[PDB]
Length: 386
Length: 148
Image (tube, rainbow over all chains, first blue to last red; front, side):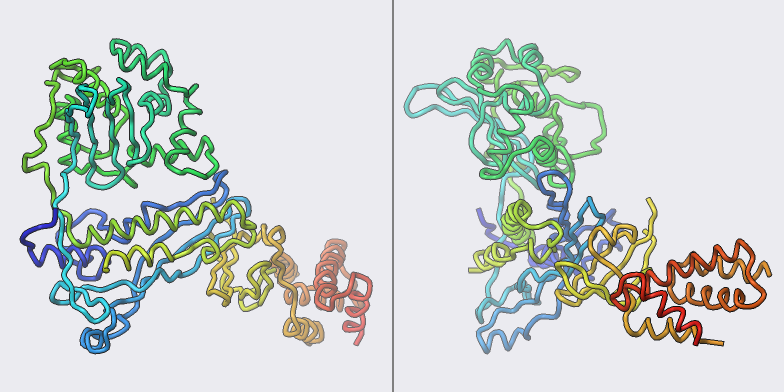
């Protein structure tokens, strides 16, 4: 849902943050912000490094910056042009075998710039981007009725401030599934195994549950390594899954600050809902293995109509659905954030082309320029402002 | 053996300018600039041969080397010790020149004859590559440069 009223300065400030401008940077310094990071800068950090198969080579990105706008606002209006500045990044390829470090400045596309008015000029026409209201970070459980089995179904979403989604559900076949980063549904035990759980510990913890026993048996995965590869096959279909890269991908998905952030309030709400770390200061806002396991147990106990639970070392909490019409469960997404998310999608596709080119290119010939295709980044921006 | 301002061929990239020699757990790094694609390449000096990068003395350098070979004590020993160390063909040249001229007259110490014989080894190895010949006619060029 788009906003019905916007605060202008919130939006213009969000854009300055996105492009990491001098005035955003100085304002951060004045507030005494700890480690100020711009929007584009954060995206580049999120994907660095891109490693090949064997962890020999890597490509990293840094220092997003702009040349001057191609043309004045009036001229863009009078000649029907797009008011924009060329975006550049520094890209660095490293061969771990030889210790070669090969770096160059890479053009990433012309980037539409916001005006004094908080507008963009796109092919001559002045336009306003509208912010959006989205669900705030937290863990949300829901109950529905199937059409048509007459069965009562349950599901849960873990929503961060920044990063991939994590969803669990009990379907009409009475199996527990996981959807990682909105991908295809997998038996939930595949995720447990991927995190290092043996069949024995899964049964110790979840053996009370009929649907969990049934899920484990019908789970066609044998061992942690197989589980890791299957998640890789789901997240990166068509690419050669390896152990080490599957570990890194899953680790970075949820459990490290690089690509995932519940933020302090989301971290608080997850603790509260699940009954974890009750008298403790919030330090990190990443997800933990403990969170994942307690979320599954919550969903499963909810399904069997239980009303309380206590995780190992935690405190008792009520087991119930979240009304999820409540305010506080809605959150503002600024224009800078919307553009930031769009860039991220473009880069992720660029990121995939890099991995694919790493499989075939001669390592001794590789530079950032031979690996980097900016078309999906350019296309993502074009789509956004159309 | 890599000097700032020299140009070297970097396979797959082309002509690279030696722009600097850094120190970067801590070893010696070549900073190379390929104008083609404005590419910066940093590579550990010891690894340069593996990657197919060689600094071969160009015509500018051959002149200088021959110019210095023709140009007109614990202190002197340690200076020359230091020149052989630097792997700079111009320094080696100075060592060869000074020791050889002394060997024609007063004669050298056993230690110095060893220093001279080694400096020549280094120098003809470098000359051989520079005149694209192979270690037989290089020394001959050296002697004639020396005799004259």
